[PDB]
Structure formats: structure tokens, C-alpha cells
Image 1 (cartoon, helix red, strand yellow):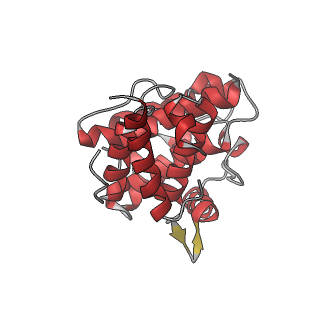
Image 2: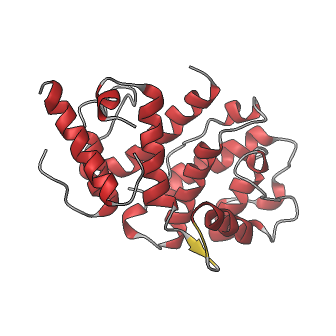
Length: 229
């Protein structure tokens, strides 16, 4: 339970499905749908463009999950436990998906010889720097009023948002505007809940990084496989 888990369940699920839809499927319950490892394997194949080992019981689920872990390991990722994944351990399942997001969607981001998390932050800063009422300094409260998200969109597609009519003191509108526009026009699923952001002063960094990284991939064209489906 908890605020962190709630945000991660929403964001991670939406991110996974932005890619799984390319493979003709999707998960519908992150606490249950990776337990048999099939969808975990399919997700890895979609975002890497590589072919994993060929995929109904206990060790059958363990085997598929292990096939997924083997692939992750061959890509340099640390490594939770296969048993805990098969058993539906929420914390560990979310942690595993985060390691996948970090490795396959953020780690390889680079701007002005800066990479991974710092690279993504700098890209955000470069894109939003022109806007006087935005000041991205982190992956949490800097995005709370919603102008940052609106700025990322406006910098790439000025006709989608009338930036000058955005008022910092109406964050619900700023957030909903960016979220709806990104979903409709950019194919970036709503990974964040506007009302829930207004209700906190500590939005989850991993959830925010995940969502912003999708804007990077939607606009850069840097990594074909990471573009939203």
C-alpha cells in the first residue's frame, strides 16, 4: 500500500502498455500479469528489438520469468528474485519494471555528453529554459504546477497549447491540459493523475522520470524501439 506504490502502479503499467500494444497485447493488473513471465518476455522483445529464448505450472512460470531475468542480466542489469515475481510480490515486481525502464529507456539517453538520469534532466532543462515561469531542477516538485509538462509539449508542437494563457495558479488545468494533449496527439498514455499531483508535494521521482522519458522518446526519434505505440 502507500502513495509511492499507487503512483508506481499507475505509471509503470501505462508505460509497459505503451509498448506491449505493439505486440498485440497488454497487461491489466501489474500485481498479477507478470507472474507467469510471458508478458515480461514480450515486453523485453518489443523495447529491445531482440529475440529472447522461446517461452502452465509453477516452474513453468518460474522458467519464463527466469528467461526474462537472463535477458536483463545479459544487458548488464543487477538483479530481485524469480520466485517473488511468480508469487506476485508487488514491491519486487515494481522494482523489476523500474530496472527495465531505467536500463532500456533512460540509461541510453545522452545530451551534451551527459547521460542517463542527468542526461534526461538536462534535456528537460534545455527544452523548458526559454519559459520564464518554469524552472526544472529535479524530477519531482519542479513539475507539480504542470507548466513544465505544457512547456515540453509547446516547445515541440506550439499549436497544441496556448502557453501564454496558462496560469501557474491553476495547476489542475495545466496538468490536465498537458496530460490530455499528450495522450490524444502524441500517443503518450496518461501515466500521472492530475488531481493526485495537486494533492501531494512529494510526487514520485521514478513515476515522473518514466513519463518525461516518454516525451523524450516521442520527440527525439533517438531510439526507434522506445517510441510510443
